[PDB]
Amino acid sequence: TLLINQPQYAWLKELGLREENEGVYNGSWGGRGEVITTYCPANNEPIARVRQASVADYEETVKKAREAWKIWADIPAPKRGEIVRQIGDALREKIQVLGSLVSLEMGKILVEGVGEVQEYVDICDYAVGLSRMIGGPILPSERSGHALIEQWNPVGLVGIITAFNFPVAVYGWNNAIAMICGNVCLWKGAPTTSLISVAVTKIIAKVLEDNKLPGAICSLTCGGADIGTAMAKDERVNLLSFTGSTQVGKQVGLMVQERFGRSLLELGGNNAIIAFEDADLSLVVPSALFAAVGTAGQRCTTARRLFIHESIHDEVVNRLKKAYAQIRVGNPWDPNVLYGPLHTKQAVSMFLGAVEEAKKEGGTVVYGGKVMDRPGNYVEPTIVTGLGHDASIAHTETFAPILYVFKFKNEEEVFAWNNEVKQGLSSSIFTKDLGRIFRWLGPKGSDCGIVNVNIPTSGAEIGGAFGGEKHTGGGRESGSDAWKQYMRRSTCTINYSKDLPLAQGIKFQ
Amino acid sequence: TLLINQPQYAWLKELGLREENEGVYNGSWGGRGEVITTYCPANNEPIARVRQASVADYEETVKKAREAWKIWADIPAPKRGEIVRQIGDALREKIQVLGSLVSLEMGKILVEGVGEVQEYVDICDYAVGLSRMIGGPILPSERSGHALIEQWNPVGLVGIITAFNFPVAVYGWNNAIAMICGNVCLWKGAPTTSLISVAVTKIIAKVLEDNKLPGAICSLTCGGADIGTAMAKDERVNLLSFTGSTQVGKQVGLMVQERFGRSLLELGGNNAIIAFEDADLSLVVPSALFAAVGTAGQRCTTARRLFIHESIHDEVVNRLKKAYAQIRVGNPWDPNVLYGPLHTKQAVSMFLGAVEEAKKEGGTVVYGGKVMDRPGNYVEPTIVTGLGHDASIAHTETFAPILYVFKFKNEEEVFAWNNEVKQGLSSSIFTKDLGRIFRWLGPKGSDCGIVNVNIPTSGAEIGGAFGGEKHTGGGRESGSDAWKQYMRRSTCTINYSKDLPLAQGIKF
Amino acid sequence: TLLINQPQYAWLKELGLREENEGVYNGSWGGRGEVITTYCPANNEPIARVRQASVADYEETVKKAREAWKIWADIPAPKRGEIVRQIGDALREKIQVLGSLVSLEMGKILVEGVGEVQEYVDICDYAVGLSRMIGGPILPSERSGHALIEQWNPVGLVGIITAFNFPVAVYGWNNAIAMICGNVCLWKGAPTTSLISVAVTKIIAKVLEDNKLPGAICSLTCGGADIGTAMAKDERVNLLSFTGSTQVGKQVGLMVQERFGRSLLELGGNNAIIAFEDADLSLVVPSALFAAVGTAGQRCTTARRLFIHESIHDEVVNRLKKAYAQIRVGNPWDPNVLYGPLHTKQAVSMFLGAVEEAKKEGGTVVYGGKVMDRPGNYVEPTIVTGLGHDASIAHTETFAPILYVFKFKNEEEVFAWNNEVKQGLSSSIFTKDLGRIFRWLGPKGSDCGIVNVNIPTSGAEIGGAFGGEKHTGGGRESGSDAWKQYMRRSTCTINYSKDLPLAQGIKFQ
Amino acid sequence: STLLINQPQYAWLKELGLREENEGVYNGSWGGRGEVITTYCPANNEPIARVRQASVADYEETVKKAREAWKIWADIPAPKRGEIVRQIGDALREKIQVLGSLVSLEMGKILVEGVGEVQEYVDICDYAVGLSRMIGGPILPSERSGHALIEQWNPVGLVGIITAFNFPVAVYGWNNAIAMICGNVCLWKGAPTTSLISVAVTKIIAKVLEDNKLPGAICSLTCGGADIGTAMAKDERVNLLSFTGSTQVGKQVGLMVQERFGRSLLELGGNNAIIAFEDADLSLVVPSALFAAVGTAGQRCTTARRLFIHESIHDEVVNRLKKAYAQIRVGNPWDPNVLYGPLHTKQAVSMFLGAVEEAKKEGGTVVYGGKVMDRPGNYVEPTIVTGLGHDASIAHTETFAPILYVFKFKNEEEVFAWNNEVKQGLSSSIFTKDLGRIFRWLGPKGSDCGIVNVNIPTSGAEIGGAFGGEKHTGGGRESGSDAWKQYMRRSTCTINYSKDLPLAQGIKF
Ligand SMILES: N[C@@H](CCCC(=O)O)C(=O)O
């Protein structure tokens, strides 16, 4: 009954997947823990099985990765760059079949699955460039015969914990950067996207092995909260990059702080789009559509709040309503399909709980609000009006496709309402006013890590640093100088002279 | 009985100090908390009194500072820099009396008191430069008609908690940088250096007043653990910069993380100097001396471990013993003096405890090891040989002037020994070998935040980022791009076109 | 006779000036060349005299500066910064009287004279910061046991030739930055602003001598074309910074290239302001006024061309005409005066030539166009309409207050019209349109070094690099990383190992 | 049968798309109405194939087509331009052995160097791809409320690239990869005697451009001699001219470009010294001197031409270098394990013999070599000359021949001055262990060269840093660090988002 044993899913073998797969890789493949079955959210059928990590597996893998680090850290960065380049090429080769696997096991539509892999490809190109550039400044010493320099060195082992909704790209951002920086990696992905984790690890393993490098440089330990907790408490994990819920993320941050580790937290969002009276509505409506119903509203960057100026409120809602009705629903791998299933059954229940609660708090469902009567975890993408900006149900990160719509009049109040939530990931305004754009980007504007103008809250490119503020956790990934989070800084002063002048002109003699 | 009431201490009035001083400043001066009396560690005589903050004082001050921020953050960064430039000049004007107050209340020698103020003057210079430079790159977008830019904005209120041993400079690092970045500051210093905190705050308050700015931009709430804990738990403190013990700092870090705040931790060090066989011994010996006994061994950057290659161990120890015997002890304001008192009687007690335990663990005191028979908190600077690199007593952070001396044979083992401690602040090797210096500065070398060659572990200049790794806490202050810790990064994409191309070429 | 001998002007003594002043400083004050008398352009009365350099003085000064360099380059950059900090303070103390001298000898109004000195103070503050920051990256080598670093070192002697129109600030830009970079400087200012050069050099000299530094670190050699030419041909002048006419600048650039020297050319502008239909006219009119008549139109950044969209052309010209009528003319040191004389009588003659040529090319003088009947070198600020955008006189830079006004309809053509001149210094558009601002700043927009939006062409701040493209010469001064032009880059590879791996994996064995 | 390309053993040439007669002009179309040149193999003096060069009209049409193509190319976002350069990188990767072999055949350098040269191109492509997501400038804090101050970078337009015989692939590649991601179009004129290499490289690039539906004139080719080169130097439509070649020609190129206020990047000759101090590791000194001197048969601009050895070790080093020279394997340069090939031309052989005779005429002792080799092709013995003084005239004439001049020295100060005393300033190396000395070498009183090395040869740079020299070497930089800024124009841009007009320096007008 496994999908992978059915003739139409034979393409899965192009990723090297079988009926039962090893979920631990450290140079060798294994897995002595529990076997998990993952399911297609589009039809609730079992795909294939993964043998997860046991305690012994985790312990062995950590030790092997750290031993592999002794070799990898000695390889010059541009040569490490060359490995990441080849990973980039290996992804390019598999991009359609890997994207199809993401569509099958996670449930996002094919163009987004392929697009997610493209993020990994892109950050590989960026990292290759970085491998020739990373480092610090030579600074002028105030002391004669001294050099003052900033050195950057790998932290060691980077633990990477990722979530179900971007089962490839987030690992990719971390992997590519942490690698060229001289670190080894240990991946624990979402249990419900284990096959994706295995498939990606198979691609990377072959590059490492083909370059006669130890596989444990990019290690994999599939597991649940037991493995993630072990990572958060493990002093041998020098940096823990965690992407997931705010609730879990807070505890991960506390555990890592308790051992004076380093953490990179990428947590939830409650992101807002704001449409001012002068906004190009031809930009607003498709932007809101993509930001809200993209990935069935299961992105951390998904727009969950839509603020519309009172003068254009009804008109925007009407046009958004017509747009929602023209969304093509189907199997996420099927063509021209723009809307797939939610990732889990539990998610469908929450969607129901939130829609009913929204009704109870005074809100009006102007579109959707119901489960689709069809196989899979399909719900109607939903629009709710009439609620206040401070309504409890709207201050609740539900990973459901529900968009809460609010009226506003003044710029000052609506900027405040953007900022009033606990999360601080993404935000966007739609406007032409020059001054307003300046204020939005300034000290009294958005408090988020991503601050956009005339585009959705979702769909970042890799060139900038990605992450948010407040309860979103403060970590940054991907571009700009996010690489510094994966390295340790040292301020080095070298005396090349025969004298000992002291800083600040202190005479100690 | 108060020193400030005696005529040979009348210079204290040049800093605006009196018999009883207000320890809360937020634009106005006050303090409803307990009155603390601070003592001169060189004679144990009371200097003057400071009325500390009550928790209600702190609450009012936080609110006023946040209101002031709304004004301050609207002032262009180069204009904020002009203010910091004037603080710089105001410090320059009072550098001698303020340095003398540092020597009187904290106990460090006058050249170090003055030198510490000079660090604040230096970072002011640096920050004035920064006020014209801070920002992020404009990046090329993969999308037609889009701009991709990185913006930096202030975090808001920066809480600053500092320790007794550097009562001016650490605040200064944080103040100058936080200010040009558009933040407001709230300072809680060490209770036993309250007068110094008040004196520094008076200097800054006058500059703010003269420039018609709200005083709460640089607020002061003198207090102890109750105020520090309030700051650690206060969601309105956007960034908490904490310098202090690893024990307290760990809890501070947890409290801040619990509320998803930002922290910058600057905690303890157990810093080593390593002298290889090819070392210039004429550099080794005075560097060890300065690193170990400067500030009477009370810096977080103090050399506490000295590894010496077998072949030169006895010669270096013998020369260091002769150098220690030439150290001139006395009142720290007497400018012929190189060595003053420990900051507290408690430090003396801990010193004696550590010396006794070192001996019980098999160490030999080859110099010092005893209290001095004079008023105040004086102990002999002390050298202990004979211990193994992993002796328990050498792995306890003792803020006292005891230098533990170890032998080694090979580079691999002694780099490991440098790295085996919980802290990771400063480290230094003395050698001429190129390959060794490369390895020391590389991925298999020192694991510390400060990695030096042929100089002490102490005495950084302000141009680089300052801080450590591991149990030192990971925070960075002062130079390089440390300013980024005082700001929030946003990645901003602006669509100037009439189209909506999506990232990664996705067709939706 | 001499103004410095009259009690109305006794404040000149505060700058250390006398009836006859030495125009050479190299540690000693001297001058064996011809004695020049400078005149106040407001009344054509002699101010004071200056003994200029002989070529022998020049020779001696170059040699003493290069000797001073051996000491100065050994001073750590942050300590050179402390010297520049003190120069900044010395300028602050004299800012009113030095500003007044600029007004007296050069002819610009008092607020502009003081402002020019303020630029020097600002760049001193900036330079003090730079003195702790200058240097280059440590890069990762592709080779084991190798370090790859970028070093920056002083070029040695920086010759600085400045023009009459900014007799303090341009030297200041060059001086503050060259000094912290570890260079010595040799200044030849405009002969007609000799007193200003002397006054500035006296301020700097006191700081150097008080610090027991060799005075030739900031040498002065007052003189004319003969000294300037010697500097251009002298191999011992490692960098020649030239600010002046494009005609002279080309020859200077050619003389420096012929000896493989370094040059930094800051030449003429033919700067345009463009007002679109959606422009805020309350910003346009006072911006055009300042940009056109500030410094009596004697800035290289002066607006000389004003393009106005057809719909608002007549309105703007009428409103500009009204603002011109309210300009207050008189002695520039008078605190109520808004408009002073041209710097020389030759400039009056050139003004007259250009106005008559504009009429002969078909232009209409709608305001001004006449020499004023009063002592000194005053002319009416002038507005000319009706010329074609490519009229010869409009494509000519005349250093006089003449503003040529053009009509346009579409953006593509007027962007081309901005770019069609030989010069490329400054440019400005007034508009609110988002897309148009993007294009203006982009590859098909303005070709100038300074590209402004909703402000005049003139009045840069110091934080950014200052300079232009095309016939403006290509040099950059002041902010950003302009400091690199005063230093030589070395790319340095250091082998710390016992092996010799070759770049690109070449095996030569 | 006479042409090598018509002989079966060289059939591999047709893998590069070469034939008996080739078109030497590419601008989207292939052509060439100019003189037909035949290039010869220097290893056997046999003709290889023919190339039809550009006429005047060809150059004229190509410049116009390139500048038309730029309108399309400059509008393509930098990261997408990077994707094109990435594909060029891949295409070179696939042809690297056969292209390297062609370099050995037509230019004469040995196979590992030919392949290594192509590897430099591949490496800079990887770097440029990274840069394509990074290039730009800082947002700076304005001193004025409601204003933004930013630095923009935009392409200059058409970049002319003139390259030399000795690096017929890599120099073009540095310029091409970087110029492309910066949004420029390029026009290449190579050495006539390496025309087939130019055509081969262009065929590889043209396929990538055409496959990507881009106008081929983006990377144009106009093979020709001095008439084409002079045209480019005088052509105002060439916005940036990058010239690699002799110093004498270079100065004339720089003068011509300055005369029209264009931009030039000059990469001219070197007279590079290695300095060995008494404490040097001689096991590094001897092979470094061997590679630096005899690699490329001494025909690099970075070739070590002067070897200074401390008096205490001079005889030992010379003796050891003699023995090393005798171990050099000579043969056909496209043969693997051959380490020494022919000079590029018969004229170079004559000039070699002349320089050797003059060296003896100046009192020099030939301790090794000095003679033509008894075999076909342009082979000479790599040569060592001792006994001369550092200022001997023959050691200050840049001969592209394998003659190493060896000097004695005693003191650090004198030998640093001797390094610096020549007119060129390209590369330099010291061999020492002394910390102070290395500090001094890299400092303001040390080497005056653009490349300043420690314990490695003068030649063999990696692409991560900027490449170029000082003084008569011309001042240009190519490849790494921020050399890309030479290919772009900087603008300092101020945007007023407010309704007010505060002026810089607080001027009230
Ligand atoms: N700060 C002045 C500098 C002008 C220089 C000049 O006119 O030559 C400005 O931006 O107008």
Image: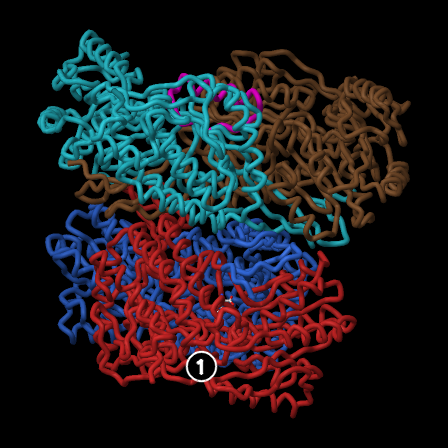
Chain colours: A brown, B cyan, C red, D blue
Q: Residue furthest top?
A: B360
B246 part of magenta stretch: yes
* Image: A62 above or below C404: above
In this view of the protein, which residue sits in the foreground, C501 or B83? B83
In this view of the protein, which residue sits in the foreground, D297 or B300? B300
Q: Residue at x 31, y 52 (%)?
A: C82
Residue C167 falls in which quadrant of the image?
bottom left
Q: Quadrant of the N terminus of chain B?
A: top left
**Which chain letter goes with mark 1?**
C
* Image: A157 above or below C455: above
Mark 1 Cβ and ligand 1 under 8 Å apart: no
Position of residue B380 in the picture relative to residue D126 (left or right): left
Q: Is residue A475 visible?
A: yes
Q: Which residue is mark 1?
A: C41
Task: Give the class, few, some or many, for how many residues have Cα within 10 Å of label 1's Cα (few <14, many ≥20).
Answer: many
Q: Position of residue D187 (x, y in %)?
A: 56, 69
Q: Position of residue A278 (x, y in %)?
A: 79, 50
Q: Is residue D9 visible?
A: no
Position of residue D2 in the picture relative to residue B346 (left or right): right
Position of residue A494 in the picture relative to residue A243 (left or right): left
Q: Of helix, strand and loop, which one carries label 1? A: loop
- Disc 1 residue type? Pro
Q: Position of residue D191 (x, y in %)?
A: 46, 71
Q: Position of residue C78 (x, y in %)?
A: 32, 50
C349 part of magenta stretch: no
Q: Quadrant of the C terminus of chain B?
A: top right
Segment tinted magenta in the rendering: B241-267
